[PDB]
Image 1: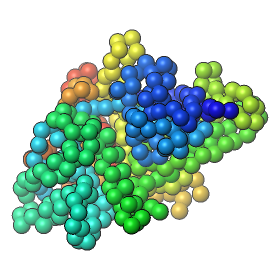
Image 2 (image 1 turned 90 degrees about the vertical axis):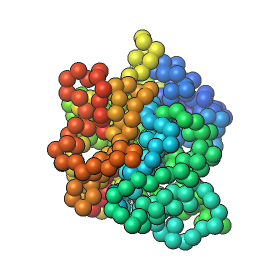
Image 3 (image 1 turned 45 degrees about the vertical axis):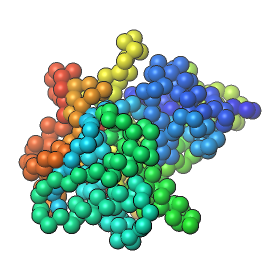
Image 4 (image 1 turned 30 degrees about the vertical axis):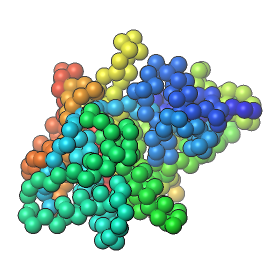
Amino acid sequence: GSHMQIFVKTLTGKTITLEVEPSDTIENVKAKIQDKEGIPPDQQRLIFAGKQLEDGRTLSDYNIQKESTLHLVLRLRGG
Amino acid sequence: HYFGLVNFGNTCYCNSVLQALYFCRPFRENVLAYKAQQKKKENLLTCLADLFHSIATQKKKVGVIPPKKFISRLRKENDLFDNYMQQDAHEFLNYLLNTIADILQEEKKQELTWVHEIFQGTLTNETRCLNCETVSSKDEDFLDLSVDVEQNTSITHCLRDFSNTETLCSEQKYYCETCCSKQEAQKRMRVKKLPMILALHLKRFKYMEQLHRYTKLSYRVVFPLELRLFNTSNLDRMYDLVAVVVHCGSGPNRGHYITIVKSHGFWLLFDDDIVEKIDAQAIEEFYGLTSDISKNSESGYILFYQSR
Ligand SMILES: [Zn+2]
């Protein structure tokens, strides 16, 4: 059992499942979301435990275990 | 008092959030208490404390303050904001709070920081396998809740919807450890610990798979002046709206941020260097568009609710 299932609460509030590994980076997680939702990884922001997850870090670095819910959000840019 | 902030190159995303936070009374007080400790080393928190102290101690009641050192520091320590491009207010909000919390944690190290005492809440996620009826509970902290929206609704609907039971079925089946296989399940996220200040982020965006782009949702989403929220046991907490960060623009790639704040019973609108008193009825403009929802909207994006 090298992998575990996490959840992503998407833009409409619909929850999707993701099959991941502790060694998966946030970019890998965004690539898996892109496979289900079509959103490019560069537009995606993931919030977990009150923190926006950083590209280059892994699920183990953030201690994202099975049944974790990541919150997916995009951006409204303004000046 | 009531001072606008200078825009230093598409920095309204930062100004609007700084104004909302200035009018979050426990946050302002803890920042001012941090300034009072008179720290010698410079970081994002000391800059924020210097800025809040300049706002608090200005000789007049109305004017303009430049957040020059704060913006300079923000650009230096974060590659993400190290540019002159337009940015998202919620991304800035979450970054600022976590950066402050890390500075405070590193100072305790040299437990919960006062940033967590103010904004942190806890959810309990419960997943019930519909095949074996096993329930798995998982607690997860938050500094804000990102809620999905719908046309002609209230933040009360969005908040209750966030905590509604969802059935996981077909492609989203849950891997149950009792069943050792994917099963239909009911997932529900309930608030276990309500925060002192509840920050609500409206997911005003929709991705169009067929068009390879996303749009801004300028939906009518009413925000009430008061909100009562419940804990899964203090059984509940009454909140009052204190600030709203508003995104102005027809789309998600460009725009302008402003903030409305409640101060001594009246509403103020802060738009970078300009401050104006606004009537309570004028805040309704920020619920979002009724008709022609593709046009330029001024819509509520981050709401700040203060517990009574
Ligand atoms: Zn089961």
